[PDB]
Amino acid sequence: PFTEIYEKESIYSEEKAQLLRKEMESVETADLEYTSFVEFTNLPKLINDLAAAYTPQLEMMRDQIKSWAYAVQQNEFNDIERIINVISSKRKEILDILALPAEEKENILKLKASLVEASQSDEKLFRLIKPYVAEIKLLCNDSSLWRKFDDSKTELILSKLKAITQFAEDLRLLKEERARTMGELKDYVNNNDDITSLLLANKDKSDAELQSLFESELAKFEPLTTRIEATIFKQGSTINGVKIELDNIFGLTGIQDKTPEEQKAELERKLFFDKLEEATTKFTIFSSDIQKGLNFYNSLLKMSKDLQNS
């Protein structure tokens, strides 16, 4: 007596759950990025090896290209290009569904279909960079063939190594700091996040806000989210600087003589072929769009099935 209080509380809890979901998505993306970096670079074994030889980049590029190509190959959706034919099939299904209705909700559905068609047209624009990259990536033979085709400076290397160590430790500490930051934010919702005892502003109305109190109560969560974003950006520039310094150290460690001009040109070509990976990532990002569009299409088809005879 009554149950409305628990309803409002449930609503506020839902909002809080949404915010925590957003923040968790952000930190998850950050952690995934840093983990991908730390996995690709292998900074620990590189530092250990360099330190051992004191007192390769090609292996890295091979590992990253192999991982990207394998991941792209596994998700059998982008390479096949059968999705357009599938869309045509879905269109045929919708055509069959459209074939004794006498209302204007069919024309509206047609308009929605038109919008989906426009979305498909927009989807076509990204096919240019995708098709060339993905097809050359799908073949192990071609990719392997193309990939295969292409003192007193010790103290500097040592200093660079030290800087790399400090940078790495700073990065790990940043990740730990973010994880703890979240841990406290989530632990703040499953603990002393108050209740309906603060809900003394009458018995709402409702629908007349009623929501300003929720926004206000949510606005005190800002100092944790801001700390999360701060640690994320800091780990961002940390990642950039560490990448730069490690690139310099890796360029000072190897040959460095150098010659010939065809050598630097070939290396340049190799670094050029690594720009395909970017397009691969882009096509991966485009994969999550075609999936959503197929979901909407299937939803529309099921909607037509229901509208036919529910």
Image (cartoon, helix red, strand yellow):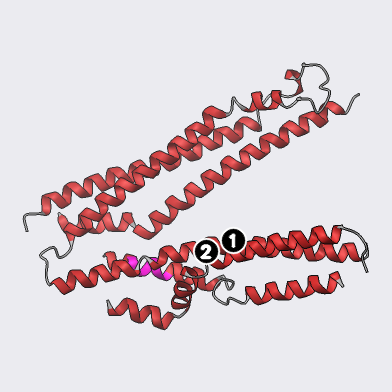
Q: Is residue 292 left or right of residue 40?
A: right
Going 52% across and 69% down the picture, which residue do you hit? 127
Q: Which residue is mark 2?
A: 284
Residue 80, magenta (yes or no) = no
Callout 2, which amino acid?
A: Thr
Q: Quadrant of the C terminus?
A: bottom right
Residue 288's mark? 1
The extreme left residue here reads 152
Q: Position of residue 232 (x, y in %)?
A: 44, 41
Q: Alpha carbon of mark 1 to alpha carbon of mark 2: how far?
A: 7 Å
Q: Are marks 1 and 2 in contact (CB under 8 Å)?
A: yes
The image quadrant that residue 206 belongs to is top right
Between 125 and 259, the one nearer to me in the picture: 125
Q: Which residues are magenta?
A: 61-66
Going 52% across and 27% down the picture, which residue do you hit? 223
Q: Is residue 59 visible?
A: no
Residue 276's mark? none
Q: Is residue 80 visible?
A: yes
Going 15% across and 56% down the picture, which residue do you hit? 54
Q: What secondary structure is found at the residue carrying circle 1?
A: helix
Between 42 and 226, the one nearer to me in the picture: 226
Tally of numbered discs: 2
